Image: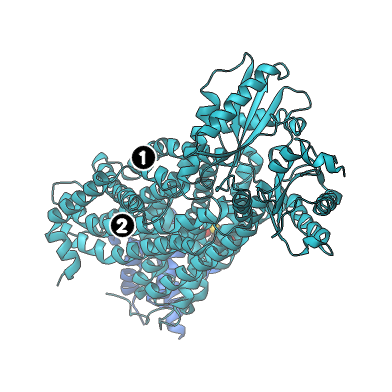
């Protein structure tokens, strides 16, 4: 009595395959490609409720000059000191920038105004910068469009001899990051397919079965990318470059892994002397639930990212889960159908090398005879990666994570060749009141606030109405001197209800010291306004330093919450399948332990060998996939253990090793190397996350599954399957005749 | 109380799974490391399966002492008669 589901798949293999390919083609043709959809559906880098963006937006609103929260800086560099022709060029550029109303919202002209010209010019006089407030929050499609428009306006124009204009800033860096990721996705896909083709030829030694698994991989990846593009195009969710890169790589990896699992079980059944129909049914009965649970675990683990706060991690959640579900559905339905329809034709899927697994016999014997020593060695090898924690540091500047020739990087280099980091990252603070603050009393109150901000350590200059160029400037005639009017216009609200300060740190503001100094300035301003008519006022502070402070605050929450959610959900799924609490706990805890080795290898390769420290994003993006895939491999091994345990513990384990040793090792290798294949991307952080996941899965395939979990199972014995009741060894059988 | 022939049949089945050597090649005279080219590790797998399926426990220390099939049967014969 064949089960109804594999029978249905086998009997209607051709209609199922045709329906799958038709649906995939419709998905991939109706909507634009994943590159275009990801470009249109780019999301803002920072949360909409972040204090920094809210402060910048409030400053723009009260001053009625812009509505955005992100700005870029146009740096003018010349071989000789800038003069009259450079000033005319700058004035024309500023006028043209202000002309583009839809993209450019406000241009803060400080160099042109003689009152604050000295602050916008380098001490060598060969450089000058202007802050331009582009439309759209950083990271959005509108922000990228505005960055492109500003770059075109500043660059594509006549220039004085020796004078060049560069556009830099966080928004430009994000735009170039997404551009580089989308450009490198094609190379990533090509290299990944070449690598998996070579390794499938190595592990199968047959071109036909390699083509079959490549067809399954193509179907799964096309379905995943098509459904993600279809849902993104209709604004179901946002997208990032990280989301698309992870979607395509994970789709390829999981499709290859499920194809490897199914074909390996089918070929083992054939090797055990079974006809094609019986072998197919055995393969389904032994692998369908395993691959279903693998897909469910990966999808749910990625979906756990949907409950974080940072937009870049939160956005990645749903698309990854949906792609994971679609690829596991394709592998579960089109997989067996393809396998049957191709095994019906000659020696198509028959095993090529009719060779046993001697080494897996040896390692199974070793792990069931001396579990303690092997377990101790494996635990030590997993924990040896923890000694790299003390030397682990993460940086937040994206300068080194992009190619040295992108326009953002060259603008960054030009700006830092003449200006300090504090100048290029000013911190903006304003005080909002309900009164007209154009009186001498309010004026020296503002002066006192500026002095209080200045007295805080680590602060270099404070620009305001009283100190237009960072230094103090009361004559009643001076209030209408045509210079105080301009200073008030540039530093005070049009209705005079708010006053703006431009705090410039002393040193590097983009660091934890800058984050502490932010609260220091907030406290200093609060103290300054105390006991004054400005007491009933609201204080807003923003800037690049504040934005990175918010990001730093978020990062720990994201890491902890995604790790905990993925852990709990994976453990729940393992309990549901294996029906054993201890086995599920072992499966989860083994990869939890291996995470240390994964992290150690990653920071050994990047921080020390390559020299580029790990980005702050790589670990949260990598832990989820590491846990999911490692738990999947352990689950496959444990399910085979449960299948073979009727012969008794300590021999069912050996049979599980010799049964799912080569296939699972090949799957782990292909997954690890296809994730490492993203190291070819121009965006360094994509390569970092890919290589981190690759090293972690390499360690999981080589150690935590071949040595850790079987030794744990042997040590626990009957208790490994608790609360299920199993015997340590079967009833002693009489010696056969 | 199992006879010598019955133990041979049980061992040969374990031999087939562990190594792949045909049951016919297994006779009490053939040596594990000279004739049957069975390494020490493969002997451990043999002991594990026999201890599980038949209950005869052979520790690691005594495993090196056994050299051919005959003394393995004698070891198993010794264990069952003591009972
Ligand atoms: C392993 C052995 C049976 C002798 O080694 P061998 O079987 O390779 O000839 C004996 O030294 C032993 O029992 N050692 C205890 C565990 C050990 O030494 N190594 C386990 C990892 S291979």
Element on which disc 1 rests: helix
Q: Residue furthest top?
A: A161
Note whether ligand 1 is within 8 Å of mark 2.
no
Residue A645 can be seen, yes or no: yes
- Answer left or right for A225 relative to A185: left
In the rendered view of the protein, which quadrant contains the C terminus of chain A?
bottom left
Tell me which chain appears blue. B
From the top left corner, tell me how far across and down residue A199 is, in percent.
Answer: 38, 42
- Mark-to-mark CA distance, 1 and 2: 20 Å
Q: Which residue is mark 2?
A: A326
Tell me which chain appears cyan. A
Observer-nearest residue: B58 or A386?
A: A386
Q: Residues within 10 Å of mark 2 (few under 14, many from 20)?
A: many
Tell me the chain of label 2: A
Q: Earlier in the sequence, mark 1 or mark 2?
A: 1
Give the quarter of the image for residue A109: top right
Q: Is residue A257 above or below residue A130?
A: below
Q: Are marks 1 and 2 in contact (CB under 8 Å)?
A: no
- Answer left or right for A368 relative to A495: left
From the top left corner, tell me how far across and down residue A84 is, in percent.
Answer: 69, 17
Give the quarter of the image for residue A12: bottom left
Tell me the chain of label 1: A
- Answer left or right for A14 relative to A679: left
Q: Is residue A550 above or below residue A476?
A: below
From the top left corner, tell me how far across and down residue A134 is, in percent.
Answer: 54, 40
Observer-nearest residue: A205 or A235?
A: A235
Observer-nearest residue: A32 or A579?
A: A32
**Picture quadrant of ligand 1:** bottom right
From the top left corner, tell me how far across and down residue A209 is, in percent.
Answer: 25, 45
Q: Is residue A222 above or below residue A168?
A: below
Q: Which residue is mark 1?
A: A193
- Answer left or right for A732 relative to A393: left
């Amino acid at each position: 009595p064949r089960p109804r589901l594999p029978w249905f798949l086998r009997t209607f293999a051709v209609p199922i395959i045709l329906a799958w390919v038709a649906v995939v083609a419709i998905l991939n043709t109706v909507v634009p490609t994943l590159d275009e959809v990801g470009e249109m559906r780019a999301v803002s880098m920072a949360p909409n409720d972040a204090p920094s963006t809210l402060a910048i937006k409030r400053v723009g609103q009260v001053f009625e000059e812009y509505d955005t929260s992100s700005s870029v800086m146009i740096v003018l560099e010349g071989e000789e000191p800038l003069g009259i022709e450079a000033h005319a060029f700058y004035d024309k550029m500023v006028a043209d920038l202000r002309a583009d109303t839809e993209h450019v919202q406000h241009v803060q002209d400080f160099w042109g105004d003689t009152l604050t010209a000295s602050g916008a010019q380098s001490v060598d006089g060969k450089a000058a910068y202007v802050q331009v407030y582009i439309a759209g929050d950083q990271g959005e499609s509108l922000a990228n469009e505005s960055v492109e428009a500003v770059r075109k306006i500043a660059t594509e124009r006549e220039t004085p001899s020796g004078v060049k204009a560069y556009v830099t800033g966080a928004a430009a860096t994000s735009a170039d990051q997404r551009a580089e990721g989308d450009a490198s996705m094609k190379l990533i896909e090509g290299v990944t397919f070449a690598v998996i083709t070579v390794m499938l030829l190595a592990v199968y030694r047959s071109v036909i079965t390699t083509l079959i698994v490549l067809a399954m991989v193509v179907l799964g990846l096309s379905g995943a990318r098509g459904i993600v593009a279809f849902l993104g195009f209709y604004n179901v969710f946002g997208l990032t470059t990280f989301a698309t890169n992870m979607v395509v790589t994970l789709a390829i990896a999981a499709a290859t892994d499920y194809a490897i699992f199914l074909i390996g079980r089918y070929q083992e059944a054939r090797r055990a002397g079974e006809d094609r129909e019986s072998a197919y049914y055995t393969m389904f009965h032994g692998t369908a639930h395993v691959v279903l649970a693998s897909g469910l675990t990966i999808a749910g683990a990625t979906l756990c990212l949907h409950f974080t706060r940072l937009p870049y991690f939160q956005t990645m959640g749903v698309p990854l889960a949906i792609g994971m579900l679609i690829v596991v559905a394709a592998a579960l339905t089109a997989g067996p159908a393809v396998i049957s329809v191709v095994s019906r034709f000659g020696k198509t899927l028959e095993p090529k090398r009719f060779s046993r697994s001697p080494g897996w016999h040896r390692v199974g014997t070793a792990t069931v005879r001396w579990p303690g020593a092997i377990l101790v060695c494996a635990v030590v090898a997993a924990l040896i990666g923890l000694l790299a924690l003390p030397g682990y540091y993460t940086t937040y500047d994206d300068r080194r994570y992009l190619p040295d020739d992108v326009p953002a990087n060259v603008g960054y280099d030009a700006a830092f060749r003449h200006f300090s980091q504090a100048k290029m990252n000013p911190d903006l603070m304003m005080v909002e009141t309900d009164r007209d603050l154009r009186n001498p009393a309010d004026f020296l109150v503002i002066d006192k606030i500026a002095k209080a901000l200045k007295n805080v350590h680590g602060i270099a200059q404070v620009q305001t109405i009283t100190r237009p160029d960072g230094d103090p400037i009361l004559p009643p005639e001076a209030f209408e001197t045509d210079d105080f009017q301009r200073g008030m216009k540039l530093f005070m609200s049009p209705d005079g209800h708010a006053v703006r300060f431009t705090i410039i740190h002393q040193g590097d503001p983009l660091t934890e010291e800058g984050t502490a100094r932010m609260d220091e300035l907030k406290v200093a301003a609060a103290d300054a306004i105390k006991g004054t008519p400005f007491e009933g006022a609201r204080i807003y502070l923003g800037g690049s330093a504040a934005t990175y402070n918010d990001m730093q605050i978020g990062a720990d929450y994201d890491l902890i919450i995604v790790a905990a959610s993925a852990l709990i959900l994976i453990f729940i799924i393992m309990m549901v399948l294996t029906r054993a609490v201890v086995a599920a706990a072992v499966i989860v805890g083994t990869v939890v332990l291996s995470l240390a080795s994964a992290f150690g290898l990653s920071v050994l390769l990047w921080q020390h060998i390559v020299g580029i420290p790990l980005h702050w994003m790589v670990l949260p993006m990598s832990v989820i996939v590491l846990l999911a895939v490692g738990a999947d491999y352990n689950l496959l091994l444990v399910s085979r253990m449960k299948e073979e345990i009727h012969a008794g513990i300590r021999t069912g384990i050996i049979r599980a090793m010799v049964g799912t040793g080569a296939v699972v090792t090949a799957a782990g290798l292909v997954f690890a190397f296809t994730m490492a294949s993203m190291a070819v991307s121009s965006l360094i952080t994509i390569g970092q996350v890919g290589t981190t996941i690759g090293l972690g899965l390499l360690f999981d395939t080589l150690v935590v599954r071949s040595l850790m979990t079987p030794s744990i199972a042997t040590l626990l014995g009957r208790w490994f399957w608790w609360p299920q009741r199993v015997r340590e060894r079967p009833v002693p059988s009489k010696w056969p005749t | 109380a199992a006879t010598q022939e019955e133990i041979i049949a049980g061992l040969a089945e374990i031999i087939e799974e562990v190594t792949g050597i045909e049951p016919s090649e297994v006779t009490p005279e053939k040596s594990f490391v000279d004739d049957l080219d069975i390494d020490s590790l493969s002997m451990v797998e043999i002991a594990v399966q026999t201890e599980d399926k038949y209950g005869v426990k052979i520790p690691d220390e005594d495993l090196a002492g056994l050299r051919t099939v005959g003394d393995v049967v004698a070891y198993i014969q010794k264990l069952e008669e003591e009972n």
